[PDB]
Length: 299
Image 1: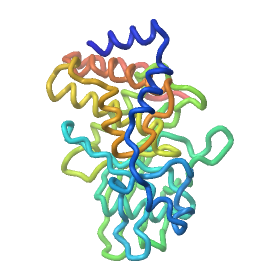
Image 2: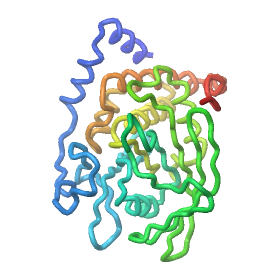
Image 3: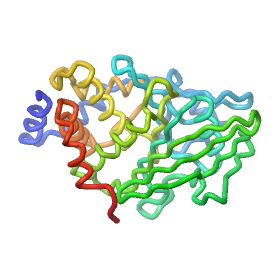
């Protein structure tokens, strides 16, 4: 793999920080005017993280269609993702409205509600079957149906009901619970296993709306997740690990949302994930059970 070669070259010459800065320098810059309107200040978690106007998700409501979320639409890979910030105490109804209107099947969460002693996200889904949530502002009902807790992630089945029409949908919630507080996993196996668990659920598929992916800001781990998935998909579509330029893929993604992949560690890790996941893609179907062997169940 030309990327495994580039990988070793970048490591040998210790130039990940400089490579990453090259990415920052070249990335698209597009206006974020709607995000910056005074009426929307309380709809944003970080003042430095905003959806571009051209790719933002619009709520289908009359009074204020703003949510901090971007449609990342990858043409060649034929895959779409919504990246959004972790919902705020006042935007949880907006978040579920978006899930409803965009017809999403999966929600992928890559952070813990509390990290480094601070609240990175609101508790936007019910933790107990018998305590459903009602979002009055967007008229939606949300019910925990079942959980399945594994060592490094949790899968939840939720039922989202439009209280207006009374239609209901099954949403799958994929919660990666063990992203380290300060660095990156440094072994991709559990990340890959988690990714493939998401893929197997059908959440990433064309017959559904785009999967919603979020961390705290929706660019760091979120970017890593989408970048790896798209690179693997592309390698798959031409069975050719060589034509896939990950840096070009990132950057293509940065046309749709700023700041995707927050540091050189996450960049390096992205290569690792893609390189390792390429073993599966290329015919070695048994590498998936090896990733699961080094994972599944332990806190």
